[PDB]
Image (cartoon, coloured by chain):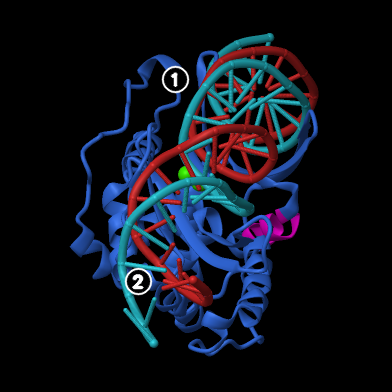
Chain colours: A blue, B cyan, C red
Amino acid sequence: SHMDLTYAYLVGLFEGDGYFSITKKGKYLTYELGIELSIKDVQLIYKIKDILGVGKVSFRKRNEIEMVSLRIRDKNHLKNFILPIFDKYPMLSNKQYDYLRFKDALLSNIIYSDDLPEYARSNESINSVDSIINTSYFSAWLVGFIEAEGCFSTYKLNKDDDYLIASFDIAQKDGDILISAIHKYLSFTTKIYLDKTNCSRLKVTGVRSVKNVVKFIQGAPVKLLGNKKLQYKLWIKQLRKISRYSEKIQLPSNY
DNA sequence: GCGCTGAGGAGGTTTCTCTGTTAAGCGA
DNA sequence: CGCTTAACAGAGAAACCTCCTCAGCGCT
Ligand SMILES: [Ca+2]
Ligand SMILES: [Ca+2]
Ligand SMILES: [Ca+2]
């Protein structure tokens, strides 16, 4: 407790799906920390807000798409509750700069739009693969980050067959270091693919990798919370039907 | 009354996620 | 051969990040 390990889960989850933003408001400035998910996670925004004790929740539907936000902008609530979290549990991607800049500005009582210095994320990495795996909270943080950015899919090759394939995938923009640390923490061997938009994309599909993914969510000191838990659990079940997996990996159903 | 504020509402954009397809590993 | 994985990657929804107007509130 204090900032009990579930607080790491959070910074992970925000790092992937959230954002620390200071925005114009005429003469004035707003400081948002917001997360904005698909409507599918209504249940979890309220979880996060329950955990945190702050922020306003809103719903939004643009064209066919229903979305939900938790948004924290009260600057007294940022100072007292949010900053000791990300100070306690700092982020691990290069978003850290977003936070640092933001904290700094907030703490200097910058209220006027024209006072605000021009900012732009350092492209330089702020961190080393090594410092990452060695990061005591990291265990916890990785559940959070997987809530946001991980993807447990199973799918069938070939279109015209019974043969399934059971996968885990995660990705970052300008996240070669971060992706590499995860990839190394879980003892993968596959290529981290690097795409046209500098997206660094991890994907594994073997039995031994998967045996490991499963291993990790199972041993990790915090559970998934949102739609992801659901996603995980169905995939588990799924894995019990494909033979290569079912025969090497302890496959519980009490997650 | 004045200056500042968070909530509310919205636009602009792109980073993912999720599900493959093709070809090559490999146990045998 | 035949079960298994590795590399590549489209596409478009689920994120990411912004700016504005408004009432209310606590100052002097
Ligand atoms: Ca994300
Ligand atoms: Ca992200
Ligand atoms: Ca997500």
Ligand 2: does it lie within 8 Å of the C-beta at label 1?
A: no
**Image quarter hosting the C terminus of chain A:** bottom right
Q: Amino acid at mark 2?
A: Leu
A200 drawn magenta? no
Write down the region rendered in magenta. A41-49
Dot 2 or dot 1, earlier in sequence: 1
Mark on residue A186?
2
* Residue A212 visible, this orientation: yes
- The residue to which callout 1 is attached is A112
Q: Position of residue A247 (x, y in %)?
A: 53, 89
Q: Amino acid at mark 1?
A: Tyr
A44 drawn magenta? yes
> The numbered mark 2 sits on a residue in which chain?
A
Secondary-structure class at tag 1: loop
Q: Nearer the viewer, residue C24 or B24?
A: B24
Q: Residue at x 38, y 32 (%)?
A: A196
